Amino acid sequence: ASMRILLSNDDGVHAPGIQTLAKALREFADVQVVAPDRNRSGASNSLTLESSLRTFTFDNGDIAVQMGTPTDCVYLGVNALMRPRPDIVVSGINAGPNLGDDVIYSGTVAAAMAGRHLGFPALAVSLNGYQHYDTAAAVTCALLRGLSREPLRTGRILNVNVPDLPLAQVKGIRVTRCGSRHPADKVIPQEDPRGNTLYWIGPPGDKYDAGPDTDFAAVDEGYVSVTPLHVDLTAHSAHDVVSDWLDSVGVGTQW
Amino acid sequence: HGMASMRILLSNDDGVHAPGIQTLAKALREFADVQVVAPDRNRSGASNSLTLESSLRTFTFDNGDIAVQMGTPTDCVYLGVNALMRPRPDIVVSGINAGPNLGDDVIYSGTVAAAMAGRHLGFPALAVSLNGYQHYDTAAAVTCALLRGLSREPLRTGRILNVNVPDLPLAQVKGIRVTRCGSRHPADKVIPQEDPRGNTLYWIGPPGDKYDAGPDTDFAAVDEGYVSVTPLHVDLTAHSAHDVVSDWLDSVGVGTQW
Ligand SMILES: [Mg+2]
Ligand SMILES: [Mg+2]
Image 1 (tube, rainbow over the protein chains, first blue to last red):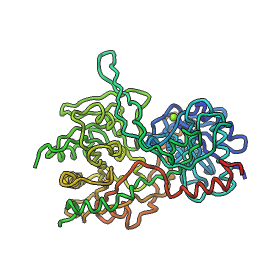
Image 2: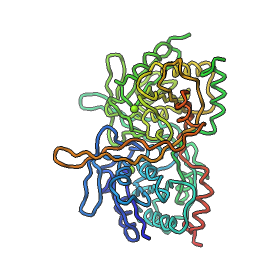
Image 3: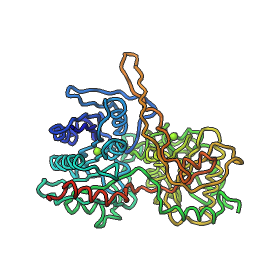
Image 4: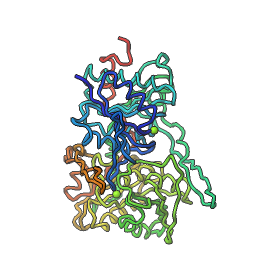
């Protein structure tokens, strides 16, 4: 009768986002934290395959995985560290948005995606700023109460982006689709003291597809954005064009 | 016709030293202008990860190959396209990977991620994976064929092609199928291993069993000795769930007062 939540993030176990959320969730749910030991923004859906992973348990039960990715954390949490397995994965609250085509790089999104085969759809929660963690926590709690009110029948992952506003100013929720950007192109070089050039990944590309039905627009307008995600990367609409193309260029056929 | 008619950024996730990338490099160099930009070590499992908290250093080998030190496959393509290469590449080719990248494994794949990073270029990017370790020459011939195809006629729709090659002599490959990604059961094994001081450390276990591996899937194509070609995109939206999620929110009163 009580929800059992595996809580992770990509900011790391000590981040205000995850700690604020953990506090809110523990009011009405059982919560196990399994999270990276440090900041893994940009970890996307990476997994540690070449080495075994070391865990550390804090006094309050929180588990940190040393050099663990967000996916590593959920993998260990679901398969080894929680008995019995969790009802759900919640990942967040992230410091900063996970919108549009940025989502494939997101560690926060990835931890949620790793929980896609559990009893409840996974939640990835990101704040569009750094101030109103309480607002994002309230939205998450509402969603979780929601999921115990009626089953959500389709969608294994919800990507939630919350405006960085006091709760009273959040206008509502929009169900959205992922927008997109032009390709990022600006690298930031910086010389080391020996005059060798090192390279920083620069800013994202300008918004391309950010119209009224997108996650970008919803957040800009002061709404919580909720996008259902899946892991199928197939571009189904391209099927026939590719097939005809192959025949036309004679690849895979003699004639 | 043409020893260097196409400019290729060649990357992988196994790293610059991998036989799969070196075999492919030799094959591509017969007709293309090839620049290798790849990880300095095996980054299998790197998915679409990228380095944000630190700057990246490059290392150039004697043959002109570039490794990005501690670089992920996405780092390599991002840097290769945006800073390192002149002229810029016409296309990204990622591979040949030692091992399959099929079904829902693709989102965790460093090989696929490199190709995905080149999706905005003149030609659609290729990720190329061999279903095993032996017949790199087979995967190379298949890759060369696709590239020659792209120079004969441009591909209209589809920005990334995920190519899986059966580990067979070329003569035994039956043909080519355009496929969709299948999917697996979740991996569920954790392999514990005590360190010298008695601490338990954990290894990620093997992939789950195939779940969706029917006749239209990448899994089935490879299993019956065909090259699988799946067009991929980066849009993670489950568009078919939109109405269900909307109706659901309303029915549970989340986001509305009533
Ligand atoms: Mg983060
Ligand atoms: Mg690999």
